[PDB]
Each structure stands twice: as C-alpha cells, then as structure tokens.
Image 1 (cartoon, helix red, strand yellow):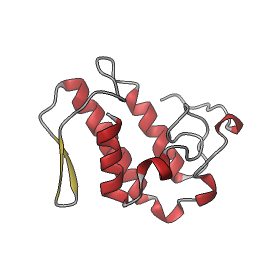
Image 2 (image 1 turned 60 degrees about the vertical axis):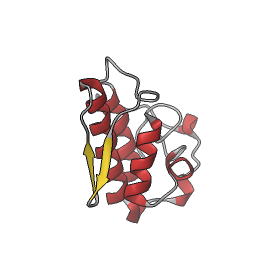
Image 3 (image 1 turned 60 degrees about the horizontal axis):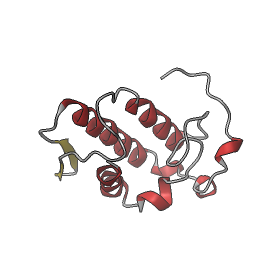
Length: 122
C-alpha cells in the first residue's frame, strides 16, 4: 500500500515521501506516466510500469509485510500479488536513493499536464 511504499522511501532516502515524490516530475505520485525528466523521474516511470503486473491486488490500499533491517528492505511472507507489490516498491525506493544526487527541487511540484506522451511500452 502507499503506507509501506512511503515508509520504504523514507527509510532509503531520509526524505518525506509525499513532499518529495508526491508530485515530482512527469511520473512520481499523482497522475500517470509520461516521458521522464531525469533519473528520479525514471525511477517513478519504472515503478508505475511494475505495478501493471498486479492483477490480483491493489497497489494503493493493500497492506503487506516487510522488514527494514541492516539497511536492506526484505519483503516478507506475503501472498503472491502482494509480494510483487512489495518488490516493485523496494526497487523504487532503492532507485530513488541511488539518484538523490540529481534530485531537482524545481521538479518537486511539477505541472503534469505539460508532460509528453511516452513512446515506451512497459
């Protein structure tokens, strides 16, 4: 759910997740996907594409188990769709951390309708 995802983002990045990634670029947070503006935004594109495999569960609402231990995210003993969701969220949080050095404050609160249609299939 958004609760696990936000916690993972906070654990990995130290950033408040909704402030920093709730409206960032063309792909993070509210709205859909569009051509990404930078590496952080690409993380968000990949993550929303990851969620396309979730046919049996709800990425926003459904809770799942994970642990934050030794600076690692370990997805727990979840049902299959929920484990897919966890693993999408984990990869995304790691991606966001990896790209902190190019996080652009000007992109934090972005005009999503100005974004361009992607030509990339998930």
